[PDB]
Image: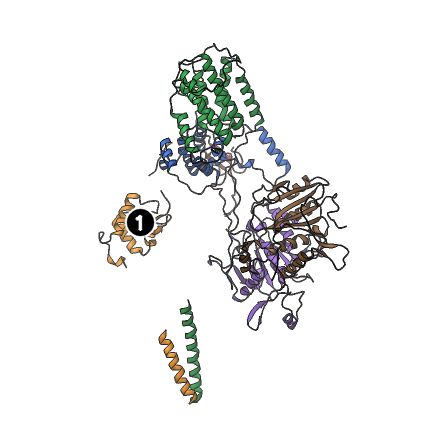
Chain colours: A orange, B purple, C brown, D blue, E red, F green, G yellow
Amino acid sequence: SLVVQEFQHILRLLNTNVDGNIKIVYALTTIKGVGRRYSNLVCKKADVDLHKRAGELTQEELERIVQIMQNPTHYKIPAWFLNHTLANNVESKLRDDLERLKKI
Amino acid sequence: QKALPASLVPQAPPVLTSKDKITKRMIVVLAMASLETHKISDKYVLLNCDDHQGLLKKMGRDISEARPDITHQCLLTLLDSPINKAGKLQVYIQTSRGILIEVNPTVRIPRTFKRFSGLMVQLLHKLSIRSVNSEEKLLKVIKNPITDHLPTKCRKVTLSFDAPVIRVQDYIEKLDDDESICVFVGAMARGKDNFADEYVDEKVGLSNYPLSASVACSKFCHGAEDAWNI
Amino acid sequence: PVLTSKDKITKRMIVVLAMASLETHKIDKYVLLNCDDHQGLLKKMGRDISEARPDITHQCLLTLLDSPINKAGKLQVYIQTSRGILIEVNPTVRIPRTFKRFSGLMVQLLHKLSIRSVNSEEKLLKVIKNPITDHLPTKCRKVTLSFDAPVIRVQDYIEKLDDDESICVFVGAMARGKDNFADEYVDEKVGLSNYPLSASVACSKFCHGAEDAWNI
Amino acid sequence: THLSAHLVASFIKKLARLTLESPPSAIVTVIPFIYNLIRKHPNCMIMLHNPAFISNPFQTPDQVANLKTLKENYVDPFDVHESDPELTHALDSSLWELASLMEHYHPNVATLAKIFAQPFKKLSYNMEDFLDWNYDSLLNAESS
Amino acid sequence: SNAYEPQLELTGATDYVRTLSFIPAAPHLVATGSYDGLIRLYDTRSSGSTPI
Amino acid sequence: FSTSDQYHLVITPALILMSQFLEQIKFNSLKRIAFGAVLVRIVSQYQRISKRYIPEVVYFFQKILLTFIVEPLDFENIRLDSYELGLPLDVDFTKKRSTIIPLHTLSTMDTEAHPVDQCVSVLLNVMESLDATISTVWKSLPAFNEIILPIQQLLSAYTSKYSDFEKPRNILNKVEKLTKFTEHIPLALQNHKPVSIPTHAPKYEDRTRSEINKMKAQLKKERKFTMKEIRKDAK
Amino acid sequence: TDRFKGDDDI
């Protein structure tokens, strides 16, 4: 009665802990700065399923995707994905003008 | 014969507050507490019986009355009673003026009376305080009536000296399964025990003796843990 | 009838406070060593700021004295202060609930070496000398509250107490400190709840259990 | 993913007697394996410790006497020369061997036994990483 | 209709129960395939603590 | 040095090295047999001062009994090193025989001149050390029963084989009464102190931005005031 | 982290 399958917890990436309990596009958008469309573009360039959670994206795919994201110039990702004293002086002037108008 | 839960590691039950209105819990209230803030010129001060006598006379009330020490030790002994370390009770302050102060079971009281009084005055003004996290407010202030702020299925009992003695262990263990308990405790130093009558269903006694309020709280709390196997 | 150390026969309760911070000072009059009344003074003699808790002592005393078994007349209170002084408290004291009045009374006690009422029929606060068994009754079972000590159930401990066997508890008045103090005195160590306590709540629950057993 | 708790406990108890007669490298290998076994199949904590034998402070002397009767009538139900993993009474016996390994002599061994002692927090130990300890290797480590 | 308390708990199994089925004709008869073999047959209208 | 401690800078490396020595070496010579025997004696010293337990030592005891009385179906699971060295029914078991007799180098050199008296002497010395270690360690240890079970089987087999010694049945009675006294409760280790509710502390009582706010409020006040006064002037 | 130790100061 022996079967055998193909994980790990939240893994850090770009000084940012990527959650271990979210979908691929979700985690990609959660990475600091990136959004949904850029996440979809990166996922499509890496050719990995987008609704697979952090349980998927085995080490080889993770490394290739990390390299692609770190080198957008080498990945040709779309560029749409990247990214007082006067008050004091006025107050003094007000003091002067108001003193003139209310005294003289 | 019967396995064990998949985990058994120690995990703290969540804090109970007024938003949860289902789980059986213990509700202790300090009533008729002598607590208010006056101004002397330049700053605001909480009344205490021993120290503010010229102005206490000027206002006209009683030195024997306006004493919040009683509140301090009662509050401390409830908050550090074992039942809270089990996480099953929360407290409500009924101000003499009428305010409701709901005390979340996550706070740590400052034990010296001057610090405590500073907390009380700051609460009376700003109506709240936050913690080291400052992510959830600690001491909240709420409206009449307490009945609107209590768990739905509960009992209404006030610990009065004149009421017949009943063993707290006995009565709690007789209390029904989803029957939460509120107890209206008269903190006021000396006088009558006829204030929460419209709220309460009965007066209850625990001895043929008179008691200090904090001691009575300790006894009743003790019976509660003894019933609840802690 | 009021119990006292002279009677060492009847079964009773004795409650002992460990190394209680009761220290006096003079500035130009006297004062209690309060960790919060002054901090530069604490650093001036260099002693730790977090040892002076006369408050802690105060509520411990308030709770104990106000416990029903007190005016039911079944216990005596003894305090071995941090400075090595034994303080005897009889069951006939109406301690002022105020901490400032408490401090004043404590300092005048420290400098009168005794307290007698205006009735003056007999003293109130007896400043007496170590050891402590010189004032424990004869058949006293000595138990210290230790946090790591196994938990016990107060009632069952009281029934396993003998018929005439008095019982003495040792509770640490000090916030931080290990329980080595009365190992020479104590017979044995017990725990009371699985969550570590206050001295106040511990002595309170224990005396309630005592009242529960002795049908108070 | 199709292993009877009895099957796993059988492997467990035989490993337990072997650890009773084991060298240290085998120990430092085996006890992470025991952890992963119990972490995956959560049930064998029964044979890690039956909870019913705890002395509950709040139960009657009748229950205490029942506990005494249970203790005096108790006997180890495991069998060894029986090799049938699904009929050996494995899930029904305690790890006194692991208690002794708790009272091992070596410090790192004592710590990795206190992990059996303490509550469960983490789930993986990488036995492939806690394997490569031979006598010479741990000698060099001690020198370091 | 009742989400909270087990309408009927059912024991008498051995180890890692991982199959059950109902009997078509009898609306009161449930078979469980435990994982130690030894198929159990239960009738609900009784106490049910043990299989039939 | 002080051995009773948990860890010692040089004692513990010595322990692991001498455990290596106990474990990996093959057992072909009575020289190596006595070498293991004295290794056992020194671990027994270390543990009469330090009070811990050695699985390798109890394994070695098993192996030594088996190699002395190898002369087989009882435990075919041991993988001995010597089958030839065995003691037939030739022992005199006279009390006046050689004791543990530590003559260390002398014994090492005269070992190849091996008499049955020397074999008996090393056997008895080893199992005296075994008795002492048992009485100082294993009845305290929880798993004592299953720890010594192979030892009990060997001792009973050797009793049946000889039944002319005394100290074997002496250890038999010792261990039997000990296991009778013991109770061997099932395990209850995993039991923890419930964790309480987290607690916190309350709060109570930029200069550039502060002065900005105060001065701006001042300015707004003044602007409102000068509006109102000019307006009254005009009316 | 906090047990029968009062509060800090400022």
Label 1 environment density (alpha carbons within 10 Å; few <14, some 14–19, many ≥20): some
Residue C134 or A1: which is nearer the viewer? Answer: C134
Query: In which quarter of the view is residue B118 placed?
Result: bottom right
Q: Is residue F77 left or right of residue B72?
A: left
**Between C59 and C19, the one nearer to me in the picture:** C19
Q: Chain of mark 1?
A: A
Give x and y (percent) for residue F4.
49, 33
Q: Position of residue F108 (x, y in %)?
A: 41, 19
Residue C90 in picture, x, y percent from top left: 71, 52
In the picture of the structure, the residue carrying the numbered disc 1 is: A50
Q: Quadrant of residue D21?
A: top left
Given the image, on which type of amino acid does mark 1 rest? Leu
Q: Quadrant of the C terminus of chain D?
A: top left
Q: Is residue C133 visible?
A: yes
Residue lying at the far top of the rendered structure: F90
Residue F146 in the figure: left or right of residue D58: left
Q: Is residue F82 left or right of residue B82?
A: left
